[PDB]
Amino acid sequence: IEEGKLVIWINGDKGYNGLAEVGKKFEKDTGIKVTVEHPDKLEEKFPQVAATGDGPDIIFWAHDRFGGYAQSGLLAEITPDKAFQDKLYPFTWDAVRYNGKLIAYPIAVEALSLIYNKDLLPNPPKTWEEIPALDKELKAKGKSALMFNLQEPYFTWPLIAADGGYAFKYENGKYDIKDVGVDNAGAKAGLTFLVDLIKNKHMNADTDYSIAEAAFNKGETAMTINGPWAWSNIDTSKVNYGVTVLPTFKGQPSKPFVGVLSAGINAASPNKELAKEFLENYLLTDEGLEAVNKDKPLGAVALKSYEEELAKDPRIAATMENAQKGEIMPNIPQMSAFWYAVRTAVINAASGRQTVDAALAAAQTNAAAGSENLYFQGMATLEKLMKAFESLKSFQQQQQQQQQQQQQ
Ligand SMILES: OC[C@H]1O[C@H](O[C@H]2[C@H](O)[C@@H](O)[C@@H](O)O[C@@H]2CO)[C@H](O)[C@@H](O)[C@@H]1O
């Protein structure tokens, strides 16, 4: 990878130009090309391209995926003096800490909130169960109650989790890597509620990120579930919008997974020296954040000096309310598998393709398995077994036939 550039990948829903403004200031001072890019599904791409001349120097993602990448030795260790570490809240350092080493620089705390249209809904609903009633209402008025991305379990998870669904059990400060609360009763109850919305045409399993965004912005649905990055496009559509706590289900709080947006450094990179300089000296400063937060919000930020300001903004105050009630994502390498399972479990359940009981039954077993790396060789084994057992039945039958034809 050409030394004396910085190539940065960051997800497209994020303030990608805000950050590219920061790579200008850097270029001004250092005279270094900073190239911000946003390829679709970077979380999946990075590991394929890492150790190559087309790897990124820096990669932005929530902390969850980084332990994955860390295990595979794709991230360089970051070694910043404690004076610096004191600039940002510790718990953010905690998120990017794997086998006691730091692997990314924390940037932003992200939690989904309930974004609602203050016109169509003067009062937004305090509970999930209120919502079918509020669709009857707005179905009539040509509108819809609620629309959020079903195609990512990030958004579906707060509901599942709400009656004590969990990914991997935390006990003795470690994650019990074979104990998984996807197919537990409250998780089952969570998903069953959501399928019942789809069953009763109160929501539509088609719904992708784009559509949900269109609908709320174009004033067609009273509610979405999203994070602060979404906020900038809704300002634009001048939709009078509030940003509140997600509603209780079975009178328990919605428990979103809380990502920490984090900037890891490609262990392949020659510019690890520069990468650190950029992130510490330019991005993680009240200037370089304000540069992004203006483009598309970071929501709540790792950097304390700035977050002190942003906290007053009662949207970011509501974002932290949701987080407080939710849970920080594990950063274990198993999360990749867990995510895949639940994506599919929720798809299948909402498409009808599988019962709720059946979908989570699988996600359980598949998440506990640890890796999506075995699906091919597994499915091949499974056929091999199926085809054998069929052969066995076939033989039972030729034998029983052959015995009837000797009794004659
Ligand atoms: O949907 C599963 C998905 O959840 C998380 O991804 C979030 C994350 O908080 C942000 O990076 C933001 O861009 O939106 C994403 C949701 O689509 C996990 O970080 C990710 O691994 C997982 O695939």
Image (cartoon, helix red, strand yellow):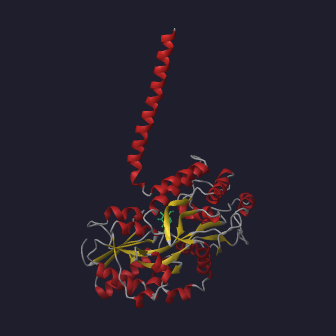
Q: Residue at x 57, y 47 (%)?
A: 354
- The answer to whether any part of residue 43 appears in the image is yes
x and y percentages locating residue 268 in the rendered image: 28, 71
Taking the image as shown, residue 88 lies to the left or right of residue 213, namely left
Judging depth in this view, the residue of 11 and 405 nearest the camera is 405
x and y percentages locating residue 397 in the rendered image: 49, 23
Specify the quadrant that holds the N terminus.
Answer: bottom left
Above or below: residue 283 compared with residue 385: below
Judging depth in this view, the residue of 278 and 141 nearest the camera is 278
Q: Residue at x 58, y 69 (%)?
A: 256
- The answer to whether any part of residue 152 appears in the image is no
Above or below: residue 380 compared with residue 337: above
Q: Residue at x 41, y 91 (%)?
A: 83
The image shows a total of numbered marks equal to 0
x and y percentages locating residue 140 in the rendered image: 74, 58
x and y percentages locating residue 393 in the rendered image: 48, 28
Q: Residue at x 50, y 87 (%)?
A: 304
Judging depth in this view, the residue of 400 and 48 nearest the camera is 400
Judging depth in this view, the residue of 120 and 88 nearest the camera is 88
